Structures are given as C-alpha cells and as structure tokens.
Image (cartoon, rainbow, N blue to C red):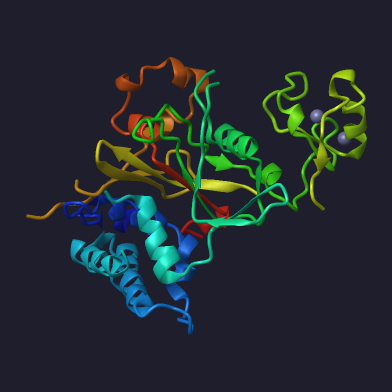
Length: 341
Ligand SMILES: [Zn+2]
Ligand SMILES: [Zn+2]
C-alpha cells in the first residue's frame, strides 16, 4: 500500500515558500478521504469563475497523482499558487480559508455554538491554555477550551483540525503537548447520550460550577442524570450551582502538521498501528521531497505523561521532539476515513 509513498522523491515537491501547502495538502490527502467530496462536487450556479479549474487542478494534477505515484510536481503546486492570487507571511490557515471557504465553497467542517447563541461555522478550532501541572493532552486541552469559552459541537465533524496554542505575545511559541491518538467528543456534542458520572446512567444535567470540585471525578466535565443531579446539589456547598439541561463517537489523530523555525513539516498516519508513522519533509534549482518512515514517534508515544514531563525535550529523537514539541496543527476524523479498507 504505502509502498508507493515512502522514500526519497516522494510526496509533494518543495519550491521556495511552498511548505505551507506541500504539508497541509499532504496531510489532507496523503492517506485520507476526509475531503474527497470537495473533489467530486459538481459546480452550481452560485460558484466562482475558477471553481472548476481549481477542482480539475487539485484533483487531477495534484491529488490523483500524489495518491497513485506518491510524488507531485512543484509545478502543479505552482499552478494552484497562481490561482490563489486571483482571490488572494502565508500560513496553513490563510491557505485553507481561501481555497475551501472562498473558492471551493466547502460546508464548514466545524459547527459550533455557545449557550443558545448563534451557531458558528468554521474550518478549524484554536485551543487556548491558561496557567495550570504536568504535560498536557489534546483531550484535556480541547475540553478546557470548550469549557472556558462555553461551547459545544452542534453536529459532529468528520474532519477536525485543531490549532495548537501559540504563546508568543501573539504567536510563535509552543509547549510540550500530547497529541491524543484518539479523541472522544461525546460530552462535547449536543444531542448525544452522555453518561452520568456517578452511576453511569444517562446524564440530563451538566453543571459548569461543578468542574472546579475535586471530589467528584476531578478534571472530568461534570454531568449527571436527573436523579444523580438532585443529590449532588442537595450538598450545602452546591445548593446554588446553576446547572442546566443537556439537550435532548471517537475521532482518530491522522496527521500532525508541525512547524520548525520558518519551515513546516508533516506527520501523517498510515495505519492503526501505534508505530504506523511517516515523516514528510517538503524541501527535503529544485528541491527533493522525502516521505520517510517514522516508527520512532511511537516508542516515545507510549510513555506516561509526567515521564514525558521529566525527560529533556532536547535530548530526544529528531522525529519525536518535533511532533511533541513543535506541533502546529493536529487533525482528526471519523475512524472510517483512512485510505485503507
Ligand atoms: Zn454543580
Ligand atoms: Zn445518575
């Protein structure tokens, strides 16, 4: 399978300032059908004059080739670059927005709302930290962000792209973060059977005021069925908690867009095996791309959080370090979405 994708002269070909495409495009289509529908979608009366060209190009000269040979000409990456300008310090974000939102007119992959407010569409989510006591997990982090900002997914995403926290005055500074091999969003989705914490029933009530209570499943979001809700709030301390009704399916990590100095690289996943990892260096008169195997980013990946905390990030592999310490985006999807059945 991935035999035609691995080695030198493999992947998307780099050209000067191309990496912010090479990488993200490699991510979104290397081994993943998540967006293949944007590829097939017929044009409709309200599309743009270069909708079609940008579809043929992307599918025909870029995605089809990369999938079938494992290589792509930086010349085709350049044909797209041109188009972009018609509509157009470039970033993966700016890139998605323009191609998907502006040209191709893809339904926003993320549907989000806070507290009976207007529903917010978007193509990726930016998670934010705030001072906390170990090495973080995307689970934790995603959850704390949805809490602090008071949000839920209206419908579940098939594609979830998560921007990592940038700590520079505005950006350009990262931490040591754990990219959860899987993502559980049940308790973050709207109309979905949530499990009452105590008995393991069907939760009818979530309460924010409870998150800060260490004595009931510390750190977990707090939700209880009707019966377990009544007890919890007959405790003198919780008499006032303004709990509310919760209204009346796991995502897999398939790609870690990373950032080094000014240069983006990509980790993609090529099989459910823990070790099933490939590194892809874009610029690895012309550059030579390299999709190299990456079983190392797995041995470290089965190491306890506060271990990853004690270990010196500098003293670790030339793969792992990057994915752990330099993660830029992490993408997730329905486990039904790899390019292998
Ligand atoms: Zn409460
Ligand atoms: Zn209960």
